[PDB]
Amino acid sequence: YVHPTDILPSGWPTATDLSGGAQPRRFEGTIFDVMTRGTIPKELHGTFYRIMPDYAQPPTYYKGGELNAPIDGDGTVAAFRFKDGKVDYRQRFVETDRFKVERRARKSMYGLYRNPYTHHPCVRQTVESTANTNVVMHAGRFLAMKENGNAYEMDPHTLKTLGYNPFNLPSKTMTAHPKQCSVTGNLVGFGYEAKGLATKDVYYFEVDPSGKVVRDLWLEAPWCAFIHDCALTPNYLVLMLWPFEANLERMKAGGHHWAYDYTKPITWITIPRGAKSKDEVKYWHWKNGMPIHTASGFEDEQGRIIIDSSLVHGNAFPFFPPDSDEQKKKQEADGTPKAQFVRWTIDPRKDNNEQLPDPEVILDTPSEFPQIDNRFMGVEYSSAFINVFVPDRSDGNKNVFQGLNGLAHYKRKEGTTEWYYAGDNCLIQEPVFSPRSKDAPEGDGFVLAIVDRLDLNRSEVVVIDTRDFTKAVAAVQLPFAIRSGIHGQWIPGEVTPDFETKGLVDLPKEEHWAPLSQSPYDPDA
Ligand SMILES: COc1cccc(C=O)c1O
Ligand SMILES: [Fe+2]
């Protein structure tokens, strides 16, 4: 059966998200008192903010949009606010400069990811960021982030866009993966390509809880590398280099910003915290592969840097292939890489010119978007909450971003892993942790994540108590599906300005519109 209206032409290209999903969503608005199944824990007090790519206009500017990447689309923030067991929701697009241009124009004006040479001539010198990767609340300011620009600030209640680069960073970029130190409260981070397209410059920074840059350093990466994420320790920021290289002449020629390079080893840059000289920075190397996201890092008793990450044994973004015909054929040959969760040891007593030890396999299954208990950010941690391909219950052939159908709770100290399965014909997104109370043990609390009910065309938020990780306590049930997203964060009420007085939805007025005389009811009747 085919419905005659279904063969009518769309002017939309295939606009995928990371999951492989291709349905544009693009709504902006609210639901007060989201339908829930089961009981919402009264211990949740805060907001789960999630950010997705969801092109607002059909991205047809360059080559009819046929090369749009899953990481490209205009950032939209879904907020799910948990107060006294009620849950409200708000979604709104980040009003990036790019968004504004395209909405006002009713027209795509931007080309390839990170390639201004493929943007419309009138926009080439704009901030090209779609601000669609990650969010943070720092020094009372709520930020949407993408690594090709500074952050945009938004109002945390209305999600109205307030401004660009609120912390006034001197770099042209900020990572979407800054870390908030649990000891100092510093937003610790960096920005690479810090001086413009294909620059090797990195700028390291620490922003104190008052919003001031208290520490910074300019340095360079050994090549212009895709430095997506990092790990924070008490004495280091550690930058994680993926084996992609940027090339200006390739960009000028209308090619991709990045090209995977099998010959590049995974490389780490140790930046001593508050370093006085770029002389203090070291490069460490292993072998080729793609560690996507760190869980976190710390320094062990002997001062060794321990980091856990996912590890994909090859290219997890095949839409950015190698330059050479030779490496192109190797990517095709390799198909879907081996995918695991691994532990790295960067011992600063050793010569950084020596190849790193092979990382230890922690989980031998496809693993991604890890989070921790943030009360342990930048110090020793045990808990990780990992998005996973469930062992024996998942495809295997799927790209790492496209078959994530469970979660894992790993605890290094106990050496145990517990597992949550999203369901048949379901996918589950990145987990976030909220502690049971202020003083609860590490990883004691509630884990939330978005579930795609693929057979129902709707999305839901599952809530799981760490005392039984196998089972959902509650499910927040949207009446629709939202885009599969990138990162999200549990943001405590206590660090949110005016969380006690402002909901995601403004209440209507108390006063009745109508006079008493209009009531159909007469108490004397
Ligand atoms: C959404 O935009 C992005 C840019 C660069 C890397 C990643 C990886 O998750 C990403 O999601
Ligand atoms: Fe990321």
Image (spheres, rainbow, N blue to C red):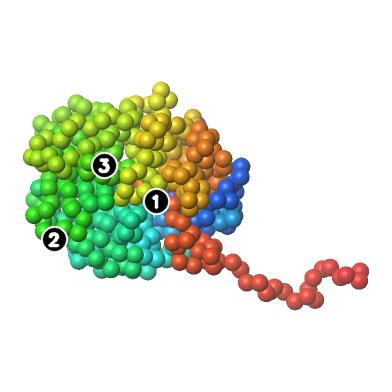
Residue name at image x 31 percent, y 50 percent: 378
Does mark 2's beta carbon lie closer than 8 Å to ligand 2? no
Task: Give the left or right position of residue 524, taking residue 62 as reference.
Answer: right
Residue name at image x 52 percent, y 40 percent: 465
Q: Which residue is mark 2?
A: 276
Does mark 3's beta carbon lie closer than 8 Å to ligand 2? no
CA–CA distance in space, label 3 to label 1: 20 Å
Q: Which residue is mark 3?
A: 301
- Measuring from the top left, give residue 381's x and y in whole percent: 35, 43
- Measuring from the top left, give residue 73's x and y in whole percent: 33, 51
Q: Earlier in the sequence, mark 2 or mark 1?
A: 2
Which amino acid type corresponds to the residue marked 1 in the rendered image? Arg
Residue name at image x 28 percent, y 68 percent: 212
Check the image and report above or below for 464 versus 489.
above
CA–CA distance in space, label 2 to label 3: 25 Å
Q: Which residue is mark 1?
A: 375
